[PDB]
Image (cartoon, rainbow, N blue to C red):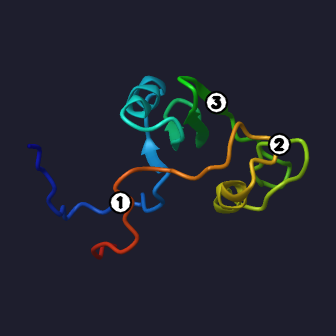
Amino acid sequence: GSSGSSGTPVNSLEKHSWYHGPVSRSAAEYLLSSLINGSFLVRESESSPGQLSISLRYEGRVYHYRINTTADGKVYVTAESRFSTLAELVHHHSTVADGLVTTLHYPAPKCNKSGPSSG
């Protein structure tokens, strides 16, 4: 038996299931171990200013995808095409790998769409 979940007053900007705010490189790899061989999460580094990365576990391996940046300010991890924003990067890919190791299907567990209010 294991229970533990209560609402907090503190405000947060981590809605997306895959998005897990700032997470230590290790934290990602480890946490992944607590999931199937088809989970993908998005961690964020502290040192570097706004440094995201998509690390999905597969066949006992963690594929890192350092999101690139264009002159303007777009994100896209591939050499076939480009994307406007991140949401589209993961959304579009979710359907087809288009280069990635696999198709982002399971971003994060206990995925919640409707939650409490906060601002």
Where does label 3 land, which residue? 64
In the rendered structure, which amino acid carries the disc numbered 3? Answer: His
Where disc 1 sits, the SS reads loop
- Residue at the (69%, 35%) spot, across then down: 66
**Residue 90 position within the rendered picture, expressed as x and y whole percent measured from the top left:** 65, 55
- Asked if 116 appears above or below 27 in the picture, the reply is below
Front-most of residues 76 and 1: 1
Q: Say which label, 3 or 1, has the lower sequence index.
A: 1
Where disc 2 sits, the SS reads loop
- Asked if 78 appears above or below 9 in the picture, the reply is above
- Residue at the (43%, 29%) spot, across then down: 24
Give the spatial CA distance, label 3 vs label 2.
12 Å
- Residue at the (81%, 41%) spot, across then down: 99
**Residue 55 position within the rendered picture, expressed as x and y whole percent measured from the top left:** 57, 35
Classify the position of the N terminus by image quarter: top left
Q: Which mark is residue 42?
A: none
- Residue at the (44%, 47%) spot, across then down: 20
Front-most of residues 48 and 6: 6
Neighbour class for label 3 at 10 Å: few (<14), some, many (≥20)? some
Q: Which mark is residue 12?
A: 1
| Residues at marks 3 and 2 touching, judged by CB atoms closer than 8 Å | no
In the rendered structure, which amino acid carries the disc numbered 2? Answer: Thr
Classify the position of the C terminus by image quarter: bottom left
Q: Say which label, 1 or 2, has the lower sequence index.
A: 1
37 sits left or right of 65 in the view: left
Where disc 3 sits, the SS reads strand
Front-most of residues 59 and 61: 59
2 sits left or right of 81 in the view: left
Neighbour class for label 1 at 10 Å: few (<14), some, many (≥20)? few
Give the spatial CA distance, label 1 vs label 2.
30 Å
For the residues carrying marks 1 and 2, which lies nearer the camera in this image? 2
